[PDB]
Amino acid sequence: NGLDTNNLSHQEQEYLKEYCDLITDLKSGDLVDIDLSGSLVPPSDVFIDVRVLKDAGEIQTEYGVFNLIKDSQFFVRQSDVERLIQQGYLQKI
Amino acid sequence: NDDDNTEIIKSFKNFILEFRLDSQFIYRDQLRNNILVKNYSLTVNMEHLIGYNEDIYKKLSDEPSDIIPLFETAITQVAKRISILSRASLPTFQLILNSNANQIPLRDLDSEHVSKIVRLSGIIISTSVLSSRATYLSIMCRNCRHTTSITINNFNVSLPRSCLSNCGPDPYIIIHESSKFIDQQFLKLQ
Amino acid sequence: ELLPYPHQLMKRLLNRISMQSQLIENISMGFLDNESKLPLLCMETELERLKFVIRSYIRCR
Amino acid sequence: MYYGISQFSEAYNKILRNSSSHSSCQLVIFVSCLNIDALCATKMLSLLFKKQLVQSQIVPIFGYSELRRHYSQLDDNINSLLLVGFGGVIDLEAFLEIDPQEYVIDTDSGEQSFRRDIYVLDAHRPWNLDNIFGSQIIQCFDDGTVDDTLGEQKEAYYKLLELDRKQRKKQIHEYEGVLEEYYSQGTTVVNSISAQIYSLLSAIGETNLSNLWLNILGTTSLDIAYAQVYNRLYPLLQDEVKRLTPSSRNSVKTPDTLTLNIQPDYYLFLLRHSSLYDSFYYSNYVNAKLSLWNENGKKRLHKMFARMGIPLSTAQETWLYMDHSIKRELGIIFDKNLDRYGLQDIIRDGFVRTLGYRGSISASEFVEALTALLEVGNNSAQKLTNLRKRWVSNFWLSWDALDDRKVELLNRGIQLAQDLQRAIFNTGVAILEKKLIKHLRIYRLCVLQDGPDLDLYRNPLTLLRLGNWLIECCAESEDKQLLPMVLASIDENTDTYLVAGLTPRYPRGLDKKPILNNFSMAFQQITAETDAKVRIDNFESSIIEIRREDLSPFLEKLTLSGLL
Amino acid sequence: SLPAHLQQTFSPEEIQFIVENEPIKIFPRITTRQKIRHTRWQLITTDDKALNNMVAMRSTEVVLWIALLLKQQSKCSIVAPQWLTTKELDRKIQYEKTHPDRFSELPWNWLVLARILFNKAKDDFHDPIHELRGKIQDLREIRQIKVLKGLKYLNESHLQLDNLSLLEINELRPFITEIMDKLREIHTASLT
Amino acid sequence: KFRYMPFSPAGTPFGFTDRRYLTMNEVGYVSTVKNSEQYSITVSFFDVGRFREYHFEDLFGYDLCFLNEKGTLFGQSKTGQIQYRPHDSIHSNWTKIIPLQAGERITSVAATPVRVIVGTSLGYFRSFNQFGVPFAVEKTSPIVALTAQNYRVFSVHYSQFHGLSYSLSELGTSSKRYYKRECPLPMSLPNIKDANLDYYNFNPMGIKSLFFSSYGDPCIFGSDNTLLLLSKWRSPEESKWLPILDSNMEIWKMSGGKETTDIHVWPLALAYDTLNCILVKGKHIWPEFPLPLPSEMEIRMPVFVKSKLLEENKEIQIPVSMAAEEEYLRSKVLSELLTDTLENDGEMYGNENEVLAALNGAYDKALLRLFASACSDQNVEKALSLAHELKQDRALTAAVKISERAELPSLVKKINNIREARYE
Ligand SMILES: [Zn+2]
C-alpha cells in the first residue's frame, strides 16, 4: 500500500489506514529523493525485457509512452516499469 | 586386465568429477548431499552418461555385471575425495540408474535379454522379508588357520575348494564378526 | 543494537543524490533539445544502486 | 531498390539516428506470428537492438486486420516501425490509411523528411509497386529482386504516374498493360528474412555463432515449401559456419563448448529424438516415396530395415539408447541401400548444433520443435479472437525456446512435434484411404468434413503441415499431373471452413523454374464478386476462412474461373 | 518494514551487490581520452577519472558493476584477477589439502566473483574455463569439509575463522549465530 | 641458403589448421580462413567505438595485409594483385596489379594517410597515393618487412649481398623527409622443435612483429624475443637501439624460473612503457583464432644476472641493488624519449609533462637508493659520481642526509659544493 479486508477488526482497519498514511508521509517529506517503499532486491540490471501480461492501453512515462498491448514484449529501463511489475501488468524478472 | 579395469574406474571417476550442465556439477552435488544425509548411493541418469561419452555407455550396456561394480568403486573413490581430508570408513556405494530406454513388456523378455540392462513395468504383488547378503567375507582355514577374504559384487562366488597354502579336502569357514553384510529383498512383479 | 544515525554523512549524500538527479535530467533535456549515451547510462544505474543502499539502510533501522 | 542489400547499413543507421535514445521507447517491431522465419529474424534483430541498448517493443500480429488495429493505436512518439514477414505485397500506404502530408516535416531543397519510418522486412513477392516506388514513407529491404527484374515495371510505373491524343492513348494503354501483367502474378517467397537480417549484421560487423544459428533456423524453415530458396542460400551458410568456427582440432567434448558443424543430416523426421523407425515412418518424403499410407508401403519400410541388417527392435529404440555401433555405421548402411529404394535424396548434409554434453540438434529438428510450439503451444467474432489470441501467445513459447537456458521448453516442442506429426499422418491416411481428394479439372480438392483431431486444423500452420504431407505424396507419384490443390477443414465451433490454396511442386530431387501460388489473387477475385462472407486477412493470403453454407458456391465460382 | 529473510543476514544478491563495488581490471574497447590536438562519466560513488581517460587496450581499473555494464556490450574485456588463474587456484588447493585446519587465503569475494565472471565474462579467461570451474568446485568442496569439522567446536565463548569467504560466512551465519546464542543462553542461565 | 617470403606484422602461419592471421597491431587484427578453393577474410578492431568489423570472400587468396586507422591494405604476393579498403566506405575501394618478374614476389606492404607502399623481393619499391595513382618507383635492398604510423614509414631490408639493414622516413603531405637510409639493423636472425622450423618456413627473418611506440618511435621484436626501440631517431648522429625488454628473461623471472618453456610472447604494440602482447602457451609459438586477451608486460632494462638471481632465490625476488640499477636506467631512457617527443612532436593527451615529472622523481629516487649502498661500502667517489647524476636539487639534499647517516663528512662537503653549483 505504500507504493480480505473483512478479516481485520475495525480497529485494525483504521490502524492500517493510519500506518499507510504514516508510510506515505515518510516518502513525501525529507528523504523523498528515494522511494523508501521500493524494492529491497538490489538493482541487478538497468535494462530488462518485460512481456505485457495484461492489457493497459497507451500510457505516458517521463519522456515517452508504453502501449501495453497484451503479449507484446518491451526492452526497457527497469526503473520505468517496476511500478507495473508490482501491479502485475508486466511479467519478466 | 587390471590396468583396463583401472582405466574403466578412472573413466567413471572423471564422469562424476567432470559432468556438468548449466554451471552445476550435478553428480558431485548429488554425491556430497547423499553423503551428508548418510545414504551411500548415487542415482545416475544414463541419458547423461550417453551424453558425456557414449563409449562408456557401450561398455556398460555390453556387460553390466562386470562394469557396474567398477562404477560403484569409482563412486566410492570420488566420495572419499569430496568428503574426507586424506593426508591429515565409508562402505561400497550403491549405483542407482534412471533411464528412458524403450520398455520391454514383462512377457516379451526372453533368452536374448540375458545379462542386458532392461527396463520394464508391472505391479508388485509380493515383497519378501529382508535378508542378509555378504559383501566382504573374512575367511579362515579350519586346519592351519590361514586367513584370507572374499570381496563380493552382488551381480553374479563361493568358498575356495581347498586351502590356498595335508590341510583337509574342503577346509574354509567364515569369520562372522569381521565379515560385512547388506540388506537384500525379493519382489514379485506381475 | 540500533546504531547511531550518520547525520552529516546522510545529509551530504542526500544533497548529492538530489544534484545528480538534476544533472541527469538536465543532460536528458539537452539530448531532447560528441553525443554518446553510455556515460549517461552509467550515471542512471549509479543512482539506482546508491538509492538502493540508502533505501535498504533506512528500512532496516 | 528502396534499400538494396549493399545499403541495409544506411537503413539501420537511420533507425539509430531517428528512433534510439536512453530517454524513451521509440521503436516498434510488428512481427507476423505463425512464421518461423519472421520469428528468427525478429530474434536476431532484438539481440542487435539489445546490444546497442535501444528501447523497443515487439508485437506479434496474426493478420492484416490486427495490423490496421495496432498501427491505428500507435503514438506519434513512435518514429520507426519494422514490419517483419508481411506487408510487402499490399499497398501499405493505402491500407494503413497514410497521408504523407500528415507525416511530412522539414522539406528544405527539392526534398522531404517524415516523422515516422515504416521499414518492411518481407520475403514475399511480387512486391506491391506503390511500396517500392510510390511511397516515400514505406522502406522495403530489397533482396535485389527489384534491380534484377523490375526495370520495365519501374519505367511503366513512373511514366504512368507522369501521364496524368494518339500518343497518350498508346502510352497509357501500354503501361496499364505492363502493370496488369506484373500484378496477377502468383505469390512466392524468394529469400529468408533471417538471411536478410544476417546480411545486415555482416554490414554492421555483428555476426556471431548465436546470430548465425538464428539465420540457419530461419532459412531452414523455408526448406519444406521453398526448396529452391534453401538451395540458393545454403552455400552462404556453409561459408559463415567455416568463418566463425574455432581453429581447434581434436576438440574434446567439454561442457562449455558450443559447436555448430556441417555434417550428414538425413531427411528423416526428428531422427535424434524419434526412434529410427519412427523417423522414417513419419517423414513426409519417405511416406511420399514408399506410399507408406498403406500396408504395402509399410511392408516396404520393414523390408528396408531388414535389408539394412537392423533388427526392428533396434530400429524402434529411441535414438540415444539405439545401438552405438548402428549409430556409427548408419551413414554406410544408408549409402549401401537407399538408392535401392529410390530414397537417395534422404542423404543430405545439414547444420547440427551440440552444446556441452546436452545432446545434438539439427536445424531441421529445431524448426520442427519451434513450429510445434507455435501450433499447439499453450459470439463468433469473440471466439475467433480468443483463438487468434492463443496463437499470438504461442509465439512467446517459440521465442523463449530459442534460448539455451530454456531447453526444457525445447523438449516440450520436440514432444508436441512428434504428436502433431502423428495427428497429421492419421488424417492423411484417412484422406487417401477414403479417397477424399476430388480431382476437379483445374485443381485437386480435399475437404475435411469430419474426423478425429479436426480441432487442430483450425490453426493455419497445422493445416499447412497436412497440405505439405499431401503435396509430397502427390508430387512423388508418376501417374499424377502436377496440379494446384485446395485443402479445406470445417470448424464445427465457428461453423466456418478454413481453406488453404496450395501450390504443387516437382519431385524433391529434380531440377526447373519455380512454381507460383495464384490462389492468392483468385480468392480475391471470387471474394470481390461474391455476396458470400469470407475473411481474407491472413498474411499468407492463399489462406481464407468462409462460412459453411458459402463454400460450395465459392468453389463452383472458383472452378469456373480461369485464373488457377 | 524489513522482510523476515533479510532481518539478520544478507541475501546472496546483496552479497553480489557488495562484491560488485570492488575494483576490477579491464581492457577497454573504446577510447574516451580526448586528444588535445560531449558527455563525461561524472560519477558520485566511484572514481570518475579512469573511465574518462580510457584508451582501447590500455588496461585500466574500474568498479566491477561498470565493467559488467561495459561487458554486457562488447565495449571491454574484464581481466580475470591473478588469483583466479589455473596455476594460482591449484596452489590454493594444495594449501587447503596440506593444512587441514587453516583456510587458505583466497580473497573474501572469491566464490562471488568466480560466479559473476564465469557467467558474464566466459570469453575473457586465458585458461580454459571448464578447468577454472572445476578447481573453484574443488576449493568449495574442500572448504566445506573444513567447515563441517569446525562446527564440532562451537562454543558459548567465541570462534575464529581466518580466511572464510563472505559468501561462505553469509551462508553459515544464521546457523552459527543461532546455535552459539542458544549455547550462551544455556550457559548464562546456569550462572547464579 | 635463403628464400624470400611475404610478411605482415604479427601474422601467423596456417600450421596444421585451415585459418591464420594476416596481421595484428595496435588497431586490430585480420584473419583468413581457407574456405575450400577461396578465402574468407575478417577484419577486426580493438576500438569498436571508432571502427566496425567487416568480412568478405577473397578469390585471390591474399597473403599480405596491413591495417592502419584509415584503411586496410591487402596483397597477393605471387600474382602482384593488391587492394586497398578505406574504413569509412565513403571513399572507394580500389584494386591494382603491380608488375613482377618471373619468381619475384611482393614481400611487404604498408599504407599511410596519403600513400600506399609496396616492396618486392627484387627490391623494387613502389609508391601510390591513397587513391591508387602511381607516384614513384625506387630500387632498394629487398624489403623483407615494412610498416607505418601516421606519416612515418619504417622498413627493414635484407639480401645475401647487403646484410640486414633498415630505413626510416616521414613522408608527409609535404616536406617529404628521410631520417635514415639502409643503415645496418642490429637485430639477430634465427639459427638454422618442429613448430619453430614451421614458423621460420613461414617467416625466415624471424621478425615476430615490427611497429612504432604510441609516441612514434620505431620498434622491432626479433628471433631473440628482445624488444628493440630506436632512441633519438629524430637526429641521426645520436640514434641508438635500446634493448628495452628481454622477454625471455622476464618470462623466466615472472614464472619463478624453473626452466620455464612452452610459453611465448607475441608482440602487438608498446604504447608508452608496456608491451601489449599475447602470451601463447604450448608447442606452437603463435596465437590461435579465438584471439586471447593481449596481456601487458612493462619494459625491463636487461641488467638481471640470471646466476645471481638463482643464488638469491634457489616467485623470484630482485635484490634492491639490481632493482635500483634497472629503475635508474629505465627511468632515464623513458624520460629521454618523452623529452624528445615533447620537444619535437608535442603533447597529444595533455598529461605527458606530469608523467615526465613523476618519472624524474623515480629516477632521482633510484639514484638515491644506489647512493645509499655506495655509502654503505664507504666509497666517497662512487657516492659522489652517483650524486652528480641527480636532477632535482631538492632531491640532492637527501643525499646530504644519507651521507650524514653514513658518517661521510667528505661526501657531505662535496655534495654541498654540488648544491652551491646547482644553485646557478
Ligand atoms: Zn589350511
Image (cartoon, helix red, strand yellow):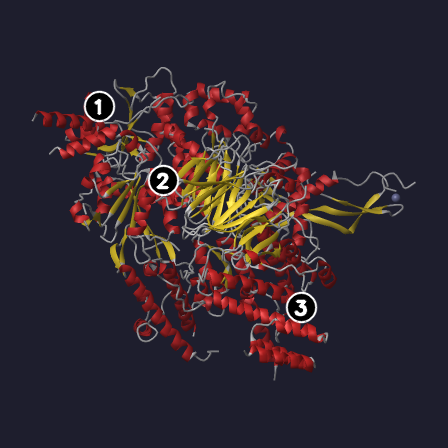
Outermost residue, front direction?
F237
**Mark 2 → mark 1, Cα distance in angstroms:** 33 Å
Q: Position of residue F336 (x, y in %)?
A: 55, 63
Give the foreground label among 1 and 3: 3
Left or right of residue D486, residue B9 in this image: right
Q: What secondary structure is found at the residue carrying circle 3?
A: helix
Location of residue E108 by image quarter: bottom right
In the rendered picture of this protein, how many numbered marks are placed on residues?
Answer: 3
Q: Nearer the viewer, residue D451 or C39?
A: C39
Residue located beneath label 2 in the image: D374
Task: For ligand 1, tell me if the residue under mark 1 lies within 8 Å.
Answer: no
Quadrant that contains the N terminus of chain A: bottom left
Q: Can you tell which mark lies on residue F320? A: 3
Q: Amino acid at mark 3?
A: Val
Q: Position of residue D167 (x, y in %)?
A: 10, 26
- Chain letter of mark 2 equals D
